[PDB]
Amino acid sequence: SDLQQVGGASARIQDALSTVLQYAEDVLSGKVSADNTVGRFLMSLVNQVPKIVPDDFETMLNSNINDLLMVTYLANLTQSQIALNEKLVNL
Amino acid sequence: QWLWDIIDEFIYQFQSFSQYRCKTAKKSEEEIDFLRSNPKIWNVHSVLNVLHSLVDKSNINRQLEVYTSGGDPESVAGEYGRHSLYKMLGYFSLVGLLRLHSLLGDYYQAIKVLENIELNKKSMYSRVPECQVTTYYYVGFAYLMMRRYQDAIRVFANILLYIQRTKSMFQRTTYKYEMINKQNEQMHALLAIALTMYPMRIDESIHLQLREKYGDKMLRMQKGDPQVYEELFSYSCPKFLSPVVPNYDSVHPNYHKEPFLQQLKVFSDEVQQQAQLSTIRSFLKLYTTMPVAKLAGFLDLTEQEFRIQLLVFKHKMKNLVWTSGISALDGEFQSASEVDFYIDKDMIHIADTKVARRYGDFFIRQIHKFEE
Amino acid sequence: GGSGDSAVKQVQIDGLVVLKIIKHYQEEGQGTEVVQGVLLGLVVEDRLEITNCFPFPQHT
Amino acid sequence: LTSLVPFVDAFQLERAIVDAARHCDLQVRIDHTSRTLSFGSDLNYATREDAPIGPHLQSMPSEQIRNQLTAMSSVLAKALEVIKPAHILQEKEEQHQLAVTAYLKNSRKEHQRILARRQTIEERKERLESLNIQREKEELEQREAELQKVR
Amino acid sequence: AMFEQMRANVGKLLKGIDRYNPENLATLERYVETQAKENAYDLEANLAVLKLYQFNPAFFQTTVTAQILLKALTNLPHTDFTLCKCMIDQAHQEERPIRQILYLGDLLETCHFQAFWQALDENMDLLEGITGFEDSVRKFICHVVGITYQHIDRWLLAEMLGDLTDSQLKMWMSKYGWSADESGQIFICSQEESIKPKNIVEKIDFDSVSSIMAS
Amino acid sequence: CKEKDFSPEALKKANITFEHMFEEVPIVIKNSHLINVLMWELEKKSAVADKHELLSLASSNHLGKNLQLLMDRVDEMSQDIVKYNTYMRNTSKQQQQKHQYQQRRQQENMQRQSRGEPPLPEEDLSKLFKPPQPPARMDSLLIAGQINTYCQNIKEFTAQNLGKLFMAQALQEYNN
């Protein structure tokens, strides 16, 4: 959970830099080392996430939501049934 | 004897206890603060709002079964014993709601329900799960009398589930518990058949044993059998106008039968049309867009012979459950196919098993509290 | 604040202790439950400040 | 693939194709009736594509996604523009180069404070709390002679 | 011009104790006839009168009871005719005009409007005393066509309306915003107005479930 | 003490009912000024020799891509759950095969003989009620059984949240 805020923190300076790198060439003559590097640096991210934009990927993902949440659901069920043997033998 | 004197022993104790709470709940916070402070058991003077009311719900129609027309006791019940408890300042605890549950207990026996817009509006006191079970019990019948059963299907599932978390521990119901379990079973079996194929809401409260039994009944009443509706009505016919119990079945008086007929004639005129409504919608909408030959494929199935095939189907389209259309140039009956979803019943029980962990963690640490 | 039952305080492990643990982390014993040492601390305010610890080399 | 793989057999080829995949070496859809063979991306990406968790091919695989990919790609590949081409971290971590240096000026004050304090602790914890381990060894001797009195 | 005048004395009557003993069949029962003359409506005023006929079957009238019944039929599909069945005994359900209008109410709520207007006595004494009953039936005729229908034939709507050909057909075509459609129809609704899926789009189930379980 | 013992000192020790998990203390919370120079190693990587700090950030992006971070743990968990629970239940059944399933027939043998002869022993009355091998609660296996199955729920609560925080982030960061 703390990695998510760290993942949002590295996200923030990326947007804080590269939107100024938009502004760099948009003022006079910036985005020189950022024209075809930061255009590639963002491409190094979007090759990882998001996948290009497939909807069957999201349908796989929403399945993989409903897969691992069902794993989380039965983890919550085995959370109880472990105790239901544990707590009955401690009456 | 052994009943009628004890009826009058109860009612005179009831109409006296109708008076002791009518006087000392309006201006006084003095006997109330006496009742909050010196008795530590909060139960007993909230028992009397349910113990004395439930047997008053018995004993009033016990005399009203004999005193059929020109009858005393419901006027003795509602106007003097119940409405005196109804319109007051609240006993600021679980008494002030249960005085309305005393009133709505006879405002349900009286079939005169419209004030369910009022009974929950002045019920701005905290809806405790002790009263919330009796809330969705009583209030859901007005939705069952609203003929909008797609909203009534969800209310009776709450009170039948009994994972609505009540625990009291001083015989609070009182002396009658599985009657509530069996009536809401029949009220939800009433709602199981009436809308299926759309529920798919018969799964949580009704368990899989009665899902098979009443669901096979749900097939047959929709496949045509009136024996299910005979089971659905006759098991439920006292369950709309029960006192809790009648007096004594006999042959000589004509009296007892006369409100027994009043229980029969009311709720058969409503649901028998719904038994025909369950037959009209019964066929699965196999395909959304029918041609005329497959319109006549379903006009065959709607009603044939012969005359009045289109107009009977017109009557059977217009039952709120067939949103359809004729393409008169194309010859293309364009209708609906409404279908539903199943799998989402794991999002509710994910916290219930987080409770089933915690509820197992609770009492055994309470056992560990008594052996610490 | 950090007491348990009548003799025990909490532990305070600074990072200079931690690095010597991750010299013998899950190596020199990977699928082998190396008891990676005994926590040599000192009893100070509310906390058992570990100062240095030594990895016990079981015959791994 | 029958032609593009010039194996000696075709039936024992396609069986050995499954004899990989039946024993979880890759993802195939071979008993399609018209004899196709798809793979999928990702769509099977748990173990069976890997043979069994470790590949035998070279790193021609594509970007697949598992647990905490999207979080940790937000960690690195979003910071991939943050460390090197930026000045926004360079102004922040040169600040942190000085923000430590304020604590490092305090660290030299702590290089004399631990010199003042924990040197005294170095001698006292060598003696005082070492007696408290020896107190646990002396109280055990105390309970032995006490038990040797009322029997 | 009579509804809101006698509404308050009725509204005080219905929300007190004034409705379990048959002594209030002279403020409410004329107010049922007030519902008749004006095509405005109160239900418990009808329903209390019915309770005073059920609890003591010695006061049971015919006109006001059918004025309860016909103002039940004007406000369909509310449960007023339901609450009509809730009190009237079956021996009281067989008296003119209680029995006939309960038979009219069988043909209205089940949408037998062909069978309604044919088996309706085309002019009957209390149909006109309830003002707008001709309107509110043909409202409730074209009500169920509004929710549960797409496209109708030119005959087929006036067939639902009853004993009409084209003129008052258009008085229930140009009233509810209905055009004509080509060869030969009335644009009741669109073709997309039929399916209307209510529960297909579910399983967005992450955010509520993980948040009660993250800790 | 000592210790947790198997058939004796397990009914006795669990009627006192000592806890099974207790006091996992909070460990590192403060700048204790042993910190000093590793703080000063942080500012340098921070600074212009910053190639080693991004490599630890590079250790994030590949920890999430291809490892069965949930599944291989859960498969070790489902291994540990299907084994250690049933053995406690094989403990719980075998004790109830002895606590009562013996004593349902032990008293049945005892009550049948009219509980003794007056002029003589009471021979078999002394012979009957021989105690079974678990008579009480088996609360040496059961305590660490109560520990390690609770430790399985920690691995569950690990596998629950680590599931969520990606099922958030994938549904999050794909969605643009």
Image (cartoon, coloured by chain):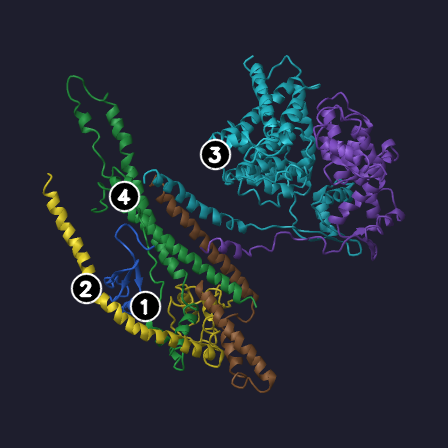
Q: Residues within 10 Å of mark 1 (few under 14, many from 20)?
A: some
| Badge 2 amino acid | Glu
Q: Residues within 10 Å of mark 4 (few under 14, many from 20)?
A: many
- Chain letter corresponding to the colour brown: A
Q: Quadrant of residue C9?
A: bottom left
Q: What is the distance, in whole Å, between disc 1 and disc 4 at their CAs?
A: 39 Å
| Badge 1 amino acid | Gly
Q: Residue at x 47, y 36 (%)?
A: B167
- Chain letter corresponding to the colour yellow: D
Chain for numbered disc 3: B
Q: What is the distance, in whole Å, between disc 4 and disc 2 at their CAs?
A: 41 Å
Q: Residues within 10 Å of mark 2 (few under 14, many from 20)?
A: few
Chain for numbered disc 2: D
**Element at badge 4?**
loop
**Element at badge 1?**
helix
Look at mark 2 in the image and give the residue it sits on: D126
Look at mark 4 in the image and give the residue it sits on: F139
Of the chain colours in the picture, the one used for chain B is cyan
**Element at badge 2?**
helix
Between B15 and E209, the residue placed more toward the observer is B15
Of the chain colours in the picture, the one used for chain F is green
Q: What is the distance, in whole Å, between disc 3 and disc 4 at their CAs?
A: 34 Å
| Badge 4 amino acid | Asp
Of the chain colours in the picture, the one used for chain C is blue
